[PDB]
Every structure is written in structure tokens, then in C-alpha cells.
Image (cartoon, coloured by chain):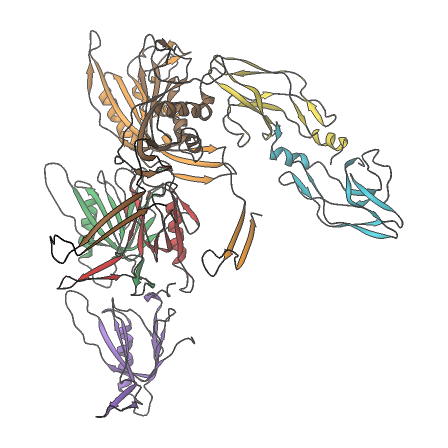
Chain colours: A orange, B brown, C red, D green, E purple, F yellow, G cyan
Amino acid sequence: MQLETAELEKGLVRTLVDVIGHRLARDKNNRPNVIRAYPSDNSNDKGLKPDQPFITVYCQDAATPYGWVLDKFVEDDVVCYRIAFQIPVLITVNGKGAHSIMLELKQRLEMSSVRDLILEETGATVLDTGAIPNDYTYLNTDFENSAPLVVTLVKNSVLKDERGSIIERVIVDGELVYEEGQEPPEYTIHLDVDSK
Amino acid sequence: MQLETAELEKGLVRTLVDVIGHRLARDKNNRPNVIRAYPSDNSNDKGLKPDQPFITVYCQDAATPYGWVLDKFVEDDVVCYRIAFQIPVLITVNGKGAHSIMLELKQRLEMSSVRDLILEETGATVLDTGAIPNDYTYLNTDFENSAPLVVTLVKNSVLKDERGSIIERVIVDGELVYEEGQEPPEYTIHLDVDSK
Amino acid sequence: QQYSPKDVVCSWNGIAIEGFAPDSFLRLQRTSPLVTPVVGAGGQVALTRNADKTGTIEIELMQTSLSNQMLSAIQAKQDNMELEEDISSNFVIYDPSGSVLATGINAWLQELPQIELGRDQNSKTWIFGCEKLDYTSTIP
Amino acid sequence: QQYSPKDVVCSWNGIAIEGFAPDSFLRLQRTSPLVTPVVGAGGQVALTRNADKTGTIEIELMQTSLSNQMLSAIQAKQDNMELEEDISSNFVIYDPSGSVLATGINAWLQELPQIELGRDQNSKTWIFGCEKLDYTSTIP
Amino acid sequence: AMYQQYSPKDVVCSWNGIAIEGFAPDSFLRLQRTSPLVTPVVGAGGQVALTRNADKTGTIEIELMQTSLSNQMLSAIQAKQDNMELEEDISSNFVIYDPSGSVLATGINAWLQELPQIELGRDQNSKTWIFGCEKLDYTSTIP
Amino acid sequence: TLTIDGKNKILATLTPTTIILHNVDPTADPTANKVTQPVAIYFSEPDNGLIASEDTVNITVPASATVSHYSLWDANDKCVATGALSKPQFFAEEGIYVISSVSVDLN
Amino acid sequence: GTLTIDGKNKILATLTPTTIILHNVDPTADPTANKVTQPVAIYFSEPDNGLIASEDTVNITVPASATVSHYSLWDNDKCVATGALSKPQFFAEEGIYVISSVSVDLN
């Protein structure tokens, strides 16, 4: 499995539709309003703001606090590497009662279930979950209630080194001497070992 | 080898074309779009922004956290000095899916290969690699996705002191005395030693 | 060449070890000093050359590193062997920059790692002993 | 799989334990080292294989965690039993990522928790002993 | 080169057909001849002559844990031997098995000699048993 | 050394059926780095130990993607041939990459 | 442009030669000309790494006063391979020519 935030966001979006979809608004296709941040298509088209309440998913960054390389192994003749990653994600609810919805979303991510569905879709484990503020932003006319939350994930990624190769034959030479630097060696041992 | 960031940047640019050139856009000459930051020529000409996605390489600074002088030796009659340096570099991807490309670039700089090619071209070793944020900047009309990364390098530089000289002859004088300050010395030893 | 933490390779018992902790993932130390001076009441000095040359090797790995399973499996096998068979093996460390020029002649596993399960992933410390901690040189 | 603090499960005496402290809620450690080397005056080395294999298990819980009542009740029952009946029970720890592969063969409650009533809710530390702190491996 | 390793776990003692187990935390066995091999005599003029003592008896001391079950078996065996008639044999070979070769000796016609002093306190006190032997042989693998 | 008749007896059973395009060299691992969906391809019966495609194959490439190699797959999802394209081609927008012809040799 | 190991393994399974014949002239021409000995059965094993090897030794009776300088493999008769023997041999009288083992490769 390779690590790609584009897939983690999609998996989280698909999971949230079932986990917390009953509290959200629904579009013309009856689907709950969960979307990825900064919507756009065809390199210039821009999405419209859905009907409230809705959810936004945005991946912040990715780091490797756990060393630099976790494993190096051979799976088939191609060499492989494994690396441990950490990915903080930001989920926000916009509308009225955003805090009341974020609280229930928090209380469900900690269940034994749900954490299995997340791993089934994204193949990642939930590591931490931060606090929830209760924000108000003026916009125009009326304030909008919002409630962000940060959910950190952990995943292992594997890549293939197509430039690598393996050793399958070894040739060894040796000598024996009574004294250091004895120019004609007392004995010479030549060895050759094949994998087969 | 002397340390010059102008050459380190060129070596990194040449290496990246092969390492991560398959994910980038290509110009009229079919070359992947990798460039040095703040392009300019003839002291006033300014380069244009290439087609996305592309990469930018910019050397931040250079420091000497490892003492001040590493070695002092004589190679030929000219005296020599060796100094240890550290050079953080900044690589950014601009376009769509910048994070997805920076992740794969990270996962390749940690391989046993690639790190050999970097040393073959620039003659420097990779020391560290920082985290990758997921930035959005408005520009005009539409946001642009970007993903910076910091790769620190280590290199040793050697310089020639043309003002130096070596000692090849020594003249020594001595005295012996029963008591301190014996004005006529008991014995005098004169010695002269040549290199030849 | 110059030092970089991505080139260090450690090998013991035929296996390779990876997944080092971010910092302070290796330590070496002799047990006794090279010389123990003795000073008499009159100020005269005589030197004693210690025959002790053992040492200790401490290596830190990530909690989920695969090398942890290999070492535990090796340790488990040695608990079901007679005293006639041996357990020592050379501990070889390679570093292109020449920062660590040493190797354990006959190295044996000594202590099991301590385990902590705090918030974030922790490290595991393995301690090996050696009969002779050799300090080699790259210059004749 | 990869480590996450929400998957660790501890079971002793048939009950389950939850309400772990935010950080450093579990610790394991052997009592004695695997091998004690001995070095003679001439530099020769001989090894002693210790038969000791006991260990200690420290677990931290929140002050209001319900598991505190269960452990206190279990301890109270054992104070009113004759020496013929036993008090040991296997201490089993499960972790899907394989970070902690160990289990106490015969574990007995050893020390009661210290209590502090500062400003905010504090933690309680329970210490168990074991006859054999086994370190298992997931690889043959 | 390094010598063979010493492992207390693989040491087994036997006497009178029973196995003695439950060694104390430290110093759980001792062996000692009674008399020295040679007793030199020096005259006033400095001349020297050697006496070769024929005594070869010895003592084997073994120290067990306070609650070790082997304490019961020894007590029962000793109780049995108090009622036996003088013409019945009470001695048996004391055998020590040690794959590390650190112990070289064995007891020929060993007998129980002293009972253990019993002491109690907050901690646990080990119990010391003492045996004699007609001949404490010293043996080793041929060099 | 094989004769022409043996070569023809051999090539008739290769039966490549589809072609996929990659951006990384698929020689070491053909399962990864796919860029386009499988497309159908047809071949003629062997002669002189050689088989050639019977017609052109139009492949649609997604926008912003690159193609540098190819691979052929059997009727039972196994990779049997790999190779490199004439040029590494970058598609600014969705387009059609035209496969003029392809052949497999035993000579 | 090259066949993968899987393609070679699939390919070799179809070549199933079962007889071998010797000639005193190179059978690169009409393969049935200059035949010197009767056909002798020969077996081959499964293809591994794109190579097949003969299962067991084969004894061929060279008629008295004959000469052998070449050989050819036959299937259902089609000759699939040809080659030259290590040395032209003059069997002044009836004798035995031994083929220790022969293999076919695609590398």
C-alpha cells in the first residue's frame, strides 16, 4: 500500500456519510453534504457552498517522526522499503448546532466499531483527537457557528526500488602467513558459493 | 573540492529530472520542468512561470555548526585547509496534486539508490528531510496548491593557502650550567638539521 | 566523506537491523580505563595496564520495527540449548565516513528491552556485551 | 499494522481494565539481566546465565475509572483467605501492532496506589509482580 | 577464547534416592576436605620432610529455601533413620550433576549429620543442611 | 537452435489480447504504475517467427498524465511482454495516443 | 521489447519434442536428408526460468561404419531444432553415442 492523501480524504469522506450522515443536510441526490476542502474541477471550475449543515475534510500535512526508514526487505527480486507516516486531518462543521454535531462525531470515532470501518476504507489507524472550539465568524449580516476538529492518522507506505539487485554468488580468496607481510603466502584458500 | 551553492543547485536540478521527472510537465524541448528560483539572465531578463506541475530549487544559507576548521595539512608544498559545511535547500512543487508528488519524492530520497546519484553529481550527503505542509495561496481567481520541503546537505570544502610555507631546516643552540644564571656556561651544544 | 545517519549499518548473527530511533540510536563504551595510575607519598608514579577490554553496545529501535521480532525469536531459541553450543557472534558496524571504527569480537545479547506504552510510539533499548571492543583505525 | 494507543487491552483475573491515563499508562521490566559477565585479571571472560526471570508490570488509570473499584474489591477478598488457596493469575496484554509481545505467567497484585488530590484529576499506579515475564515473538 | 558459561538452573543434587531442589538465593552449596594433603615438617637445620595425610573425609553443605518442599522429605528420611537398628546401612552416595563442569567432586558413602537451624522473621531465612562423606573424591575430564 | 517451424508452433500460443500503458518502467513490476485502462489488440498468425498487429489501437490518456512504456496481457491476466515507447509523452489535456503497430520476434 | 519470464514459461510448455535423430550433414537443409540413425525417445521437464532440460540420459545406436556430425530434434513429426555435435565421429564399427543431457533456452 502506498500513502496518498488524495485517497485518505476520499476514504474519510465515504466513511463519514455513514457515520454521521443522519445529522447533516442532503443535496438534490439525497446524499449527505460532505465534501473536500477547496472544491474545484477542470483546473478552473469552483464548487458552490452546499446547504448547511455540512462537513469539510482537509489534509494539513504529513511527517515522519518515527525515524526515516522502518523496514528494508526483498519481496520478489525487486527491493522494497517501508516508511511510517503521520497525517493530521481537519474536519469542520458549518451551520447551526455545529458543536452539538462535532461532540457526537467525537463520541463515535472512539468506539471499537467505526475505527474498523476507517481502517477498512483508508487502511489507517486513528492515533489522537484534539479538542473542539466553538467559533463564530461574522461573514455578512449574520454570524456562522463552526466547530473544527483535528484527527491524526498513522499509515505505513511501501515503495519498489526498480534499480536494486541481489547477490546470488560470492567469490572469496584468502591467505595464511606465519609473519605479517610474508610475501609468498604459506597457503591460499579459494572458494566459490552459488545460491543454487 | 570547493563548496559552491551555484553548483549544488545545478546538481540537484539535474538529479531531479531523472528521479521525479515522470510526474512533471514538459516544455517545448520535452525536458521536465525543473528550475532554479528567481530565474534571470543578462542581469535584467526575467524568466516566465513554466507550465504546471513544476519544481523550484532554492538554497537558503550555509553554516558551520561543526567547529571552525576540520583539518589542516600539506598537499604539495602549498598548505591546505578543510572545513565542514551544512546547506539547507528548499524544494517546492506547484500545481495540482503537489502533495501527492512531494510524498513520492520523499519516499525516493531515502532509498539506498538516488542518494548515490546525488553524491555522484553534487558530491554531498543527505542529512535530514523535514515535514511537508499542504499550502493553498489565492493568487487571483483560483487557489494554487503547493508543497514545500527542506532537504539538508553536508559537504567538505578545501582551499589553498598560497601565502604559506614549510620549515625544512632547523638551527638549535643550548647551554648547560651547574647553577641558574651561570654567566659562562659549562658547555654549549650547537646543532643543525636539514630535511635532505 | 562526511557523516550522515542514513549510512550506518549494523549486523549481528547474520541478520540486518533497521528502524533506528530518530536520535541517540547507538552507543559504545569500554568497561575499564586503559591505564590506572598509582601515586606514592613521595610523588613517584607507576602505571598499571589493565587487561580488561570488554565493552557494552546499546542500540535503540522503534517499537514497531520488524527487527524487534527477530531479536526476540533469536533470544527464545537460545533458552532451549545446552551449554555446549555457543551463543556469541561478531557485532559488525559499518559507516562510510569513518566516525565509528569499532567492532565487537564475541558479542552476546545481555538485556531485554524496557517497554512503555505512552501517547506516541516509544523506543526499545537492546544491550549487548562483548569480549573485546576493538577500536580500529583507517591509517597504517 | 501500526501502533495506536486505542487498541491496547489488558486483562487480569477475568476482568477487563480501561480508563488508562493519557500517557505512560503501562510499563514492563525484567528484574535481572540475561547474562552477567565475569572478567579475570588476565582478560579472560566467562558468562553466567541467570535463572531469575521475574518482572514488574506498572499500569496507570484515571482517579475515577471504574477499574479502581474492581481492583480494590479483589484485593479486599484476598485478605480473608487461607494460605492454601492461590492468588496468582495470568496477566494478558493484547496489541494488534505487535509493539508489546509479553505476558505475565503468574501475576500477583503487589502494591496499592498512591493517592493525590491536587487541583485536577490525578492518576493511580497499580504494581503487579510475575513469576515469569515472557517475551514472545510473532516470527517462527 | 572464553570459558564455558555457568548456569545455576541446570544443577541437580540427589541423595538416598530423592532429589534435593529449591536452592536458596545465593551460596547454595559448599564442599570442603577436612585435612590438607601434605603436612611439612622442618628441622632446626632447615631440612624438610613431608607427611602424607591419609584422611580424606569431607563435608557437603546445602542451603535451601524456607518453604522448599525438599525440607519435608529430608525430615521424613531422618525420622525413619532414628528407628533403624545399628546393623542397617544409613549411608548413600551423594551425586551432583552439573553440565558446566564447575563442580568436580562427589560424595562416597555420605550421611546426614546436622539438622537445619530454624529462624523466622519478616523475611525468609534459608535452612542449612550438613552431610558427611567417607571420601570426597575429586574428578575431572582427562586433560 | 530452433527452426522456423518450431518458432511458428511456439508463437501461435502466446495469444496477447490487451495492452496497458505505464509511466515507470514495468519490467521489474508490471502490476504498478498503470496509467490507462486496458484496451483490446489483435495479432495475425505467426510467420518467419514473427507476429504483427492486425490494426491500429486508439488509447485514451487522462489529462496531466505521462506515458513512457507499455505491456501486453493474456486472456488470463498475465504480463508477457514489455517495452518502451519512442518518446516520453506528456498530455496537457485528454487525447488519443495512436498505436500504429507492434510485433514480437524470435529471430 | 522483450518477453517476460512468465511469457517464456508459458511459451516453452508447447514445445514437446519426443525423438532425436542424428545426421552426417547439417540438417539445416531439408531436415529428413542424410539421416544416419533410427529415432530414439527423449523426455523433457517442466519449464523453469525459461529453460527446459532433458529428464534422463539417452543411448543411440550408431550403425557400423557410419559417421555422425550433427543432430536434430523431432516431435507430429516436424523438426523443431537442429545443431552440430561437439565432434564428428567415425564409428568404424557399431557403437553407442551418449547424450548426457540437452536443454532448450529462450534467453
Q: Nearer the viewer, residue A152 or B72?
A: B72
Residue C132 place in picture, x, y as percent: 34, 57
Q: Quadrant of the N terminus of chain D?
A: top left
Residue G58 place in picture, x, y as percent: 77, 49
The quarter holding residue C38 reads bottom left
Q: Nearer the viewer, residue D98 or G36?
A: G36
The residue at the point 44 percent across, 23 percent down is B14
State the count of labels: 0
Do we see residue A14 in this rendering? no
Residue A8 is left or right of residue D27, and the answer is: right
Q: Nearer the viewer, residue A102 or E39?
A: E39
Residue F97 is left or right of residue E94, and the answer is: right
Residue B52 place in picture, x, y as percent: 41, 15
The residue at the point 88 percent across, 49 percent down is G63
Do we see residue G46 in this rendering? yes
Q: Determine whether B142 is above or below G28 in the image.
A: above
The quarter holding residue C85 reads bottom left
Farthest residue in the front direction?
A: B184
Q: Determine whether C50 is above or below C72 in the image.
A: below
Q: Nearer the viewer, residue G54 or E24?
A: G54
Residue A139 is left or right of residue B20, and the answer is: left
The residue at the point 42 percent across, 52 percent down is C13
Residue C39 place in picture, x, y as percent: 17, 61
The residue at the point 31 percent across, 90 percent down is E54
Residue A180 is left or right of residue F85, and the answer is: left
The quarter holding residue B53 reads top left
Q: Determine whether B137 is above or below F4 in the image.
A: above
